[PDB]
């Protein structure tokens, strides 16, 4: 009841919320950094090395053993850029046809595709799917290759699990990429895309649910890239309407903006 | 009186933040070194034939140097028992050398010659890492425990910078589940090591920070409470603050101490 006890109640909410936001941001940063390393791994060991040291079995083993390096990711995979002129060749060599993600059916003719050729076993269902056949993934692929940096999607429901999450995509370039490249040069030099699924729904719940005081607090995360159209990234709910705190979150993609809001159940 | 209280609060805040930064950067480096140990296992031992070589290791480690902020370099030393030495040297077209003089190694029961190296530590190639006592002890404890280990602070090769070495064991696929120490030794393939150059890279980390001229910072290895060893700072023997550090090796203990000059 007391006004003095209310000041401390807010102080505790601020502290709890700020700590959770720091944990989320730090663990995502750690995961992005290890995805960057995987992109370098594919470049060095698959493309640069003659012959390639990476087959599906090798990729699966390495990513399984390093899963702890990528705490907020449910799986990683590598999609190769295939232009239509090359598609029949690519399919004959791999002995499978490029499929659409919505039904796993053979892809119709498209100018280019991004079929998954290597996958962590946790996302084995991605193998042979054209990652340009989902709009969130397609937009991510384009912005990754044009900018040279890790990029994030808006929140959407992921394949197979239908869990609400975001996808992280990094470009992989050919050795022909010029120094100080233009966007056009980046596109021309694109080899493929290293993608990771941030399963926010399952993995952020797991992270938050183990923390002391979790039952006292309601935590929501929003994508606020468009101020007038906030999108739920994490969270549902009967909460305390009188008091809230907003904690800062920076997931590292300047194209996107996010925030965390905590309230008491009370 | 009020100003003395504020002075204490600033000291605690300054010291705690530096400790956090140092612990976090150490942690990130340790984790990325662990990934490299896994990479050598997967590519050099699990694949047959081996699908990693010096060229590839040098490229990958150069390109990922940013992932390992406090490390001057990383290298992989392979376990070689004496009966295998002749075959090993013929395969590599070099002789196993001592760390102190680069002379051909006398006969030893076993050796840990560096076979892969980041170019920043290229001078380690062919050196027997068991011919230096800090590295030797680290190698033994790494392989017997199955986990990352740290040395005491000591002066590193070439640069003479005061630092600590981080060593991870790499095992053969014959390693049993829930292995004994004896099983770990038998299954050892080699050792992935990284040099934490404290004298240079921690100075770079902490030295640039605002407020640095107002305080004295030390990091101590306090594994032996009665014989603390300087890891960072000067050799000097009221108002101090101790901030916690955990560098991840249960065998070792560390602390940061900060004081005002006046
Ligand atoms: C480029 C690449 C391999 C992206 C990874 N994308 C995805 N990874 C895993 N699940 C998903 N569901 C929808 N998109 C998903
Ligand atoms: C096992 C392994 C390769 C250890 C790395 N050890 C070291 N690495 C870099 N420089 C050093 N100077 C002395 N020991 C050093």
Image (cartoon, coloured by chain):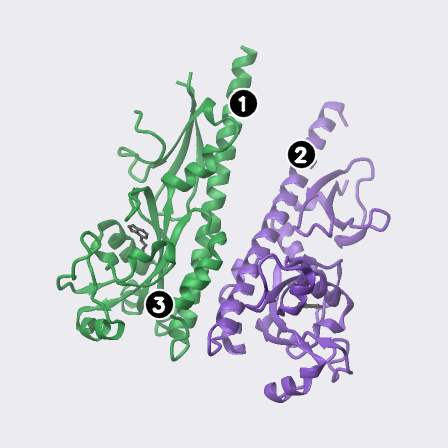
Chain colours: A purple, B green
- Report whether residue B251 is seen: no
Marks 2 and 1 on same chain: no
- Image point 68% across, 41% down: which residue? A17
Task: Confirm if mark 3 falls within 8 A of ligand 2.
Answer: no
Chain ID for label 3?
Answer: B
| Image position, residue B3 (x, y; %) | 55, 13
Of residues B180 and A103, the one drawn nearer to the viewer in this rendering = A103
Can you name the residue that lies furthest to the right here? A228
Chain ID for label 2?
Answer: A
* Quarter of the image where the C terminus of chain A is located: top right
Of residues A262 and B172, the one drawn nearer to the viewer in this rendering = B172
How far apart, in angstroms, are the residues tagged by discs 2 and 3? 47 Å
In the picture, measured across the screen, residue A108 lies left or right of residue B63, that is: right
Which residue in the structure is indicated by mark 3?
B171
Of residues A102 and B119, the one drawn nearer to the viewer in this rendering = B119
- Report whether residue B261 is seen: yes
Q: Which mark is residue B9?
A: 1
Q: Earlier in the sequence, mark 3 or mark 1?
A: 1
Can you name the residue that lies furthest to the left here? B106
Label 2: how many residues lie within 10 Å, few (<14), some (14-19) or many (20+)?
Answer: few
Which residue in the structure is indicated by mark 2?
A12
Q: Secondary structure at mark 2?
A: helix
* Quarter of the image where the N terminus of chain A is located: top right
In the picture, measured across the screen, residue B214 lies left or right of residue A225, that is: left
| Image position, residue A167 (x, y; %) | 68, 62
Asked if A174 appears above or below A199 in the picture, the reply is: below
Q: Secondary structure at mark 1?
A: helix
Asked if A17 appears above or below B38 in the picture, the reply is: above
């Amino acid at each position: 009841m007391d006004d003095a006890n209310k000041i401390r109640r807010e102080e505790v909410l601020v502290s709890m919320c700020d700590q959770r936001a720091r944990m989320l941001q730090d663990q995502f940063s750690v995961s992005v950094n290890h995805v960057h390393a995987l992109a370098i791994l594919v470049s060095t060991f698959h493309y640069h090395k003659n012959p390639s040291a990476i087959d599906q079995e090798t990729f699966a083993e390495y990513t399984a053993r390093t899963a702890f390096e990528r705490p907020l990711l449910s799986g990683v995979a590598y999609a190769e850029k295939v232009v239509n002129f090359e598609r029949e060749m690519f399919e004959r060599q791999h002995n499978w046809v490029i499929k659409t993600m919505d039904r796993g059916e053979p892809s119709p003719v498209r100018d280019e595709y991004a079929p998954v050729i290597f996958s962590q076993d946790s996302v084995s269902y991605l193998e042979s799917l054209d990652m340009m056949s989902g709009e969130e993934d397609r937009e991510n692929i384009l912005r990754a290759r044009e900018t040279g940096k890790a990029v994030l999607t808006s929140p959407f429901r992921l394949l197979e699990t239908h869990h609400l999450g975001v996808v992280l995509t990094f470009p992989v370039y050919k050795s022909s990429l010029p120094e100080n490249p233009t966007v056009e040069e980046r596109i021309a030099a694109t080899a493929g895309y290293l993608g990771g699924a941030f399963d926010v729904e399952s993995l952020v719940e797991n992270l938050l649910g183990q923390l002391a005081g979790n039952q006292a607090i309601v935590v929501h995360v929003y994508d606020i890239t468009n101020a007038s159209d906030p999108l739920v990234m994490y969270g549902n709910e009967e909460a305390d309407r009188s008091l809230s705190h907003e904690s800062k979150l920076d997931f590292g993609d300047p194209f996107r903006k996010h925030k965390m809001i905590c309230r008491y159940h009370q």
